[PDB]
Image (cartoon, rainbow over all chains, first blue to last red; front, side, top):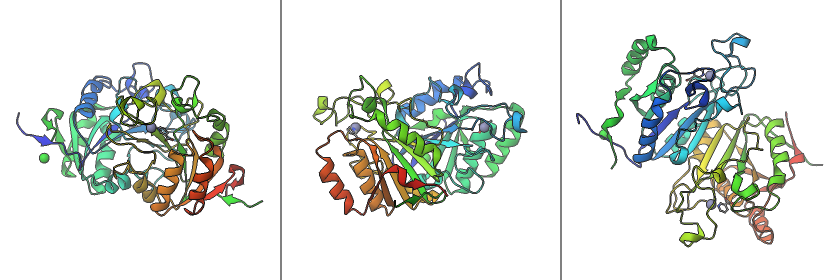
Length: 200
Length: 199
Ligand SMILES: O=C(O)c1cccnc1
Ligand SMILES: O=C(O)c1cccnc1
Ligand SMILES: [Cl-]
Ligand SMILES: [Zn+2]
Ligand SMILES: [Zn+2]
């Protein structure tokens, strides 16, 4: 192609962000346009490349969470714990996924990052990854302007190389694409089309 | 009447392999009395202020080395993406912060939730250390495999371990005697879940 990126089984990790019914199904609280289209591509990357580790994330709010309009927050209720919408989408292939990590778990605070949670408090993701030798993390999924954005940014904050799989992501708001992209690039995240990836 | 108060800063709960195959009717590898645990683990999971709670999952490829069909001990069980591999619907996942899969490659097994049989780490240790876990509570199945080895590995990684003896069932009841001895002087504490209290 134009450039080659070798995926390493010792050193490269993959994060699959909020691929859940509530974000992806037509019915469902917070539908992200072009959400389901990503499945095809993500399923293939998880499938055919040999990452050291793979993590999918899960927005996992209580019935009465702070970020809901019913309690003063920006969003409609979504990804309530044990609700159908909170489940990972049936079209996702979890077979090569070593861990599911949950966020937004406490009534009082929201989390867009896969790394932090209840304020200062960690999810232990940064820890586990480091602990297992991972040096460079790839990110795909939803929402580009939220979970993907902050997860990629906290990964830099924690010392990882970050590569965002450009074509395997979608946003709540496309007007935010300019703003967010700049912020990513200037924080040293490298955006990249998945078709540039090859195995060892 | 000797209690154990559970901390929201240091104490972490591990629920071991509460999946369809070990538990449900027509599951391929049945742990006797495994379904009956569901009441108590749900209570411990929801009534206690653990820092963190982790559900493990046996998660095997369809041609796994540990299957009898390939010369291992066990019927095909917990195949990746199968009815059988799912966590039992009757377990309340609401207060679980993470699910960890194990026995994930064809060529290696892993009774422990800490390490695959070939030294590869699952990441569990680093996660628990990251959040500041200082002791782990273990419950689920199987007492004589997953639960035993997790306990021991938690002890190698330098965690205190309390084992909820009433919230476990074993694949094999006779083995119970040999495992508890090994756990006893592994420094592990055996405790009925009705000894746990909050803050
Ligand atoms: O993608 C996310 O992180 C997100 C977006 C809206 C609501 N909850 C989570
Ligand atoms: O107890 C376990 O984890 C176990 C037992 C048999 C087969 N696979 C896993
Ligand atoms: Cl490279
Ligand atoms: Zn949310
Ligand atoms: Zn097994």
